[PDB]
Length: 16
Length: 215
Length: 228
Image (tube, rainbow over all chains, first blue to last red; front, top):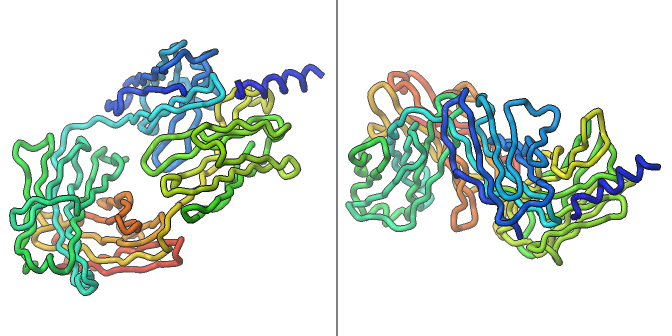
């Protein structure tokens, strides 16, 4: 789901 | 493609009341990724709800969204004047996002019959070689009105167009205009010109007529 | 903040290609989804596609695929919607929409839905030629008058493109005024009417003038409407 991707990214940037 | 079906088409009710708008998807909306937007007349959409239940911060408590899977409902608890607008539902549970055709929330008032006025083609226009008779249905409710053009008793075929205002912010009525367009002649080879109107507020049609002369 | 600012209106031609821009200012750009959503004259919202500026992750709608491109300029925080093979049907208002983030406390965490919008951009696709309107008086007659009320107006006819704005007596006439949405005639030109109800005892003792403003044409006429 294209609309989810930005979550994948915000979780990484936060992660590290 | 997922189809979002919004109903009713137009929900008409008094202020201070509660509004429940229905949105039903042709398929199961995954993770309940459903949003409700409010578009006021001349503006852009304003996000009201997302994830079916979630409300952003800035959106007043009046607005609540519920439902899931395939049945969603938007709820305003106590309508404020500004809440009378259009509402759209959008699904983003899959890549191809889609909107519902939308639902209008109208102010409900007491039925009012159209005040019919009629205007003959201006001389300034006839000098151009084209005529336009205008028929104004002013300040009526509801918005469903039937207009019919009649020249020398002859009924008319697709040579007229009508436009309808949006509900009035002040008195909640609608106004409509029906323009009949002709060439200088045959406007000049016909006598009487009339428009008759049918509205839920009238028992008999109302016919406004004029004959080339007065004034 | 998070402000989205779109480019000015556009008048393209059937077959042509149009490019609209969106400027984001007051929040992260590269990491949030940016979609384009249009709205045809007197219709609902249609989602066309989007893009995540970072890796230029694009998502196009089938109805448009192989005809539309969506771009991001991270170095300038700007987005671009380009659409070719323009048909009159594509005449609509194109919106730039950026998704919201959890708790505006502040920017951080996507939510999919579109919390931010541009002012909208009017794109008109016609083979017609820009022209100011002919303004004809809808004169007060015995057939436009009843009791203490009398309706008068003016027909703004044959102009292009949208929009036109009307006012009466330099704005010195507000209530009783109804200006109808324009309708597309067959010639491809628009036309509409502006009416207002006034006391009939004041017809001779007053003068009524409709001021028309068609900016896309640099036109600004004023017509005097008086009895038949």
